[PDB]
Amino acid sequence: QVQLQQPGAELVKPGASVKLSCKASGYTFTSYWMHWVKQRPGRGLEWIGRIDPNSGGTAYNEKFKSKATLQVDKPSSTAYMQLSSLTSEDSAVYYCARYDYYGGSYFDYWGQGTTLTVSSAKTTPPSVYPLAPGSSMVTLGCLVKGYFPEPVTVVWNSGSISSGVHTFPAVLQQGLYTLSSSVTVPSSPWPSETVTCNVAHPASSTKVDKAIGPR
Amino acid sequence: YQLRPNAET
Amino acid sequence: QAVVTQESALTTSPGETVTLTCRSSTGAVTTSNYANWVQEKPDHLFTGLIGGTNNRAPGVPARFSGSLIGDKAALTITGGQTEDEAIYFCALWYSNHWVFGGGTKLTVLGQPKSSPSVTLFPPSSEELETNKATLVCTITDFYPGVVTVDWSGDGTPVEQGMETTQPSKQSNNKYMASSYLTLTARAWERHSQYSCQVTHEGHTVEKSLSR
Ligand SMILES: [Zn+2]
Ligand SMILES: [Zn+2]
């Protein structure tokens, strides 16, 4: 029942600043230190600093003292970290981790991290292309090419086909995302009966349905 | 080269 | 960063003992470095296990212990379990700041090795109409979760215009991944052989297509 909750993602433009939140529940907020860690899948984890909710006591990584600011709000039991003068280099997942300090010295519970994307790129709808072969059994796909920002939702036949499908994570080249979804069906249903992928990209108020036709 | 405990730890 | 280093990756089996280590570049890891060991399982699920070198964090399995070995910090897992397959991070204290290590990806053989299922997709003529060609190569059902995905154009290795996703855990606990090779329609009209090569556990496999 010890829990730390962090928003899933946040989009911001360079030069802006954000205020990440970490809701604490399941324990007495004031008797545990709270730490913030930055992760850029690429070159690991970096310790930002720590704040003592009880005394307001603060401790920052020298490399982050002009970049971050930590505080908390006791009544709501939530810790905050504001990042300023945002840049692309600030893009990453930010975690809040609960910390015990007594005759102890730990990091026990961690929130799940808020992935911050700092980019001045324009909202771009995805181009949905059918993935078919040209000679269970047959594997069909959908390419969701060049969109921004994330995310996009991919379903098959509105959610009629749920197993055999593999929706891969997005790769990013050029400041534009791309991913693809696969669904394997018996060589009987296709092309006999129909298979369709439904791609939704709310950010661009777009939605595309592609029937996968024989090649 | 850093290390140890302190009053910050 | 102040630089703590760990074993890149290690492999064990259910019921065995495996030990992970942690180096400080400054010198011998000491009790004053308050070694911390953290676990990261699929979908950024981080959990502290050990603190202050050997203090087990409440609500952590007894099979996890911490210590020093030579001039390094150690995380010992006795009687390894399938669920222990995850990434382990070391964290040392240097007077006024914490420094994490790169993390050790631990594999706990908990199931049979499963060869990769590879599918190569040609570019859609819809995408070809805009003048662009994208080759899609999906790789699924492999275990352990390490594969090397290479691209070839006319039997020649390709580095640029290619992105690969880091292996992903499937529902059935096996792994999956995908690779993309982007070309201009014109650059795709002049070459004939296109192949996605996947190396897994010392075994190589290819899926090719000739426009
Ligand atoms: Zn990392
Ligand atoms: Zn501290």
Image: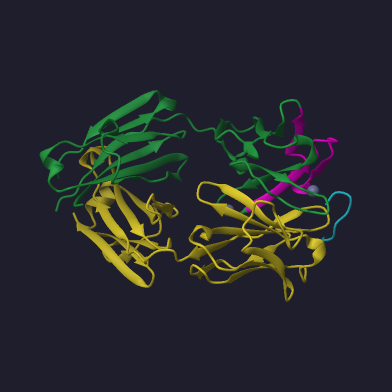
A204 within the magenta span = no
Left or right: where does residue A51 sit relative to residue A197? right
A64 within the magenta span = yes
Q: Position of residue C42 (x, y in %)?
A: 50, 50
Establish if C28 lies above or below C88. Answer: below
Residue at point 36%, 33% (across, down):
A126
Magenta-drawn segment? A45-74
> Which color has been applied to chain C in this rendered view?
yellow
Q: Nearer the viewer, residue A17 or A184?
A: A184
Q: Is residue A26 visible?
A: yes
- Who's green, chain-wise? A
Q: Is residue C193 visible?
A: no
> Which color has been applied to chain B in this rendered view?
cyan
Q: Position of residue A87 (x, y in %)?
A: 63, 38
Which quarter of the picture shows residue A196? top left
- The N terminus of chain A, quarter of image: top right
Establish if C129 lies above or below C181. Answer: above
Residue at point 64%, 30% (across, down):
A16
